[PDB]
Amino acid sequence: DTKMDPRDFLQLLKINAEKAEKNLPLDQKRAGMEALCERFPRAEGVELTLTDLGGVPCIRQATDGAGAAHILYFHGGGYISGSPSTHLVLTTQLAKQSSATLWSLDYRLAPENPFPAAVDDCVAAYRALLKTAGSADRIIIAGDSAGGGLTTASMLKAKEDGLPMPAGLVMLSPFVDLTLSRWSNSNLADRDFLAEPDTLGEMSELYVGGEDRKNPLISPVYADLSGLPEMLIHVGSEEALLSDSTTLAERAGAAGVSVELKIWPDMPHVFQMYGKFVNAADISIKEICHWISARIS
Image (cartoon, rainbow, N blue to C red; front, side, top):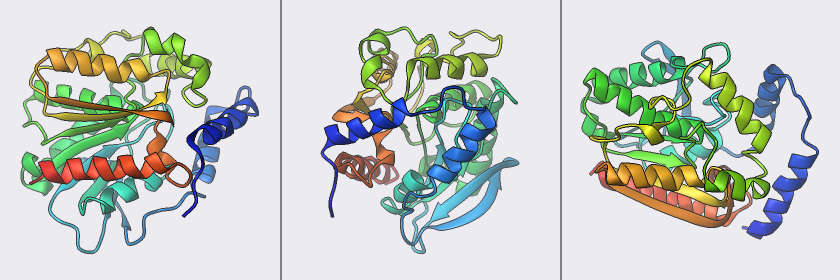
């Protein structure tokens, strides 16, 4: 079917950015994210079981004939928004193109619960998911933006605690440096009509809550990423957070982790959400799944 020329779509995200609301109450910005992200298409044949993990709410997802593999998923939303719901668009596709049961976790958001609330839930869930899954070998962790920072964060916290490392980590435009201070952050700020300057600011501020911005469990890009499992990273070119994806790859790289990074031309922050319009959205999903299942094999 028909698609948008990447650039034009950017022009679309740009126009939407301009008319964006000035100071929208956090509770409404949320409600409208749900309303909005509900007009998007959910993969067909993906039953949405409303279950839980470690007492943390989650929308399990799987096709009728799903394998034994498992994807514990953390959504994005600057740590202050988003929900398993909002991301069905992406996860339903992930769960289907990989024949795996995907567990979209509803970890707590800030300011109601700042760090380490979310990280904590991600661990608890994993811990739970190990038992259910049977082996850490058939599990994979994934998330977009902030959700990408938790897929690492939680695994570092898990290593600390003493749990076995998953088979792999998949991150989409990871948000891993809350100091908002690297090359892309300033150089591409204009180009990013989603992860905006003032946006990330309060985003970080609220999540950090007094705590230290360079706390490894908050901005993994400063951690001892040693011991973590292989990680795949996809990121768009039009991203202020581009340098997070490259810097986390560098460190984890030098930290001794296996890393695969792909930077997609003309794609915006977490483009995998806009399959509806841009082709790469699909190519990426397909590549992310070929990657996942190959690991759980």
